[PDB]
Length: 207
Ligand code: NA
Image (tube, rainbow, N blue to C red):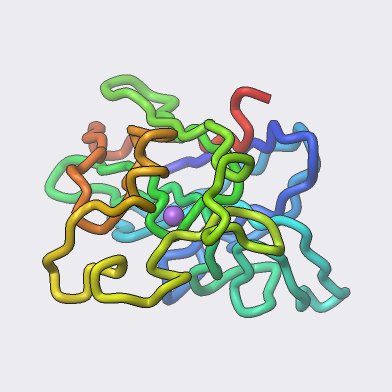
């Protein structure tokens, strides 16, 4: 499958793509404002994620740091990134269908639209000013709005026992972005697309 990743933000981001134990395609790249990066993700990939990283510094070997979404200090990510990260999540060719969502379970850093470029399903978006409105206790100094599990490390926010309810903090993310997961047991906002669809992830879609 093809994913086109587009930076419509006015600032540079460092896109990342991983399935947790491996890079997808090159795994990461700098995107200046307006740039597009096309990657190829193998059919059958389960548990892939795409995210943006902000305020990164990398040397000539591809090592460095980012203030949001850092993946072990690498430009080309082979594992998932440090919160806060708005996440585009997908599993492809699962019994004939692809499944896509946006999640705020690991917080929010950059607004996002995740849409198919082929026909048969709709896209999803979280483009509200979550960072500007972020509750004081969730605000990350490096930028972004953390989720409550990252900040407080309780069974209730992290849903560790498999039973948890919504919280004041999850309801904040849900009020601003209804179409994104706000906590682990949120009613699913996953979209079912035909198997082998192609997609576009746009950062700052309303920029
Ligand atoms: Na998230």
